[PDB]
Amino acid sequence: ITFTVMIVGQSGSGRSTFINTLLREETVDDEGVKIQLNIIDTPGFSLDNSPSFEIISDYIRHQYDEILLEESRGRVHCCLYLINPTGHGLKEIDVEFIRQLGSLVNIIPVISKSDSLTRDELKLNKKLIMEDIDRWNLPIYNFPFDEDEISDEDYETNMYLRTLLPFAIIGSNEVYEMGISDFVILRNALLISHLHDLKNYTHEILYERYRTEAL
């Protein structure tokens, strides 16, 4: 079971060191069965450095184009948008990127250089990025769940995952919190299940909207 995850975000901190904390492609098991993850990185952008995102937008659209093509005779299931912190909430480029591409790819916001900030600094930045997501109605993957199927306790876990957003993912992968533990290392089973929901979300609805756009 192959999976496509793309890393997008500014040079600022280090978009090149982030892939290591897990254009260039890189490949990396369930409850016995083999699961090969195909992570792909893009160049870091700055509003003036605009010709670097149109090719990401093209790649995404083009992957969805070659499926729709095969259905008439490789697509990205998750976007890890690296946000540079400190700089009060979300930038105009961070905003303009995720509103367009948020309809085509499952964007999940992450925070770069997490270890170079305090807990109070991190709480703040988390609060603001989320405040700018609401204000600009930014279409982010907010862990949608099957109302009847994925029920109770697993719901409580999903409410907690959403809480960790924007993911400050550092060290041995790990996500940082604010309040039992400071670093959260996701159950191998849990990460895979979500990957299956992003794989399914980009096929069941995200490709469906793009298919009913050209048709």
Image (cartoon, rainbow, N blue to C red):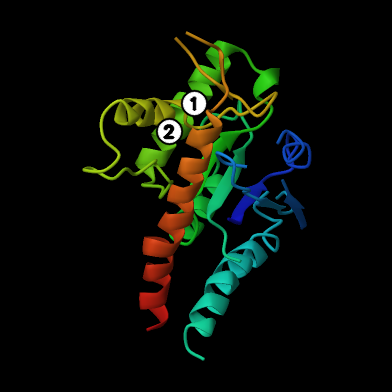
Residue type pointed to by label 1: Lys
Instruction: Please name the residue shown 56% across and 33% down the image.
Output: 188
- Per the model, the C-alpha gap separating discs 2 and 1 is 6 Å
Residue 47 to residue 56: above or below: above
- Which residue is at a point 51% across and 91% down the rendered structure image? 73
Q: Nearer the viewer, residue 208 or 134?
A: 208
Q: Report crowding for label 1: few under 14, some 14 to 19, many 20 or more residues within 10 A (C-alpha).
A: many
Q: Position of residue 15 (x, y in %)?
A: 73, 41
Q: Position of residue 167 (x, y in %)?
A: 54, 31
Above or below — where is 176 with respect to 139? above
Checking the image for residue 186, the label placed there is: none
144 relative to 27 in the view: left or right: left
- Amino acid type of disc 2? Met
Instruction: Please report contact status of discs 2 and 1: CB closer than 8 Å, yes or no.
Output: yes
Residue ranking furthest to the front = 32
What residue do we see at 52% from left, 25% from top?
Answer: 125
Q: Which residue is mark 2?
A: 130
Query: Is residue 176 depicted above or below 105 in this figure?
Result: above
Split into 4 quadrants, where in the image is the N terminus? bottom right
Q: Position of residue 184 (x, y in %)?
A: 55, 20
Residue at 59% over, 41% down: 32
As drawn, 68 above or below 26: below
Residue tagged by mark 1?
A: 126
User: Callout 2: 10 Å neighbours few (<14), some, many (20+)?
Assistant: some
Residue lying farthest left?
148
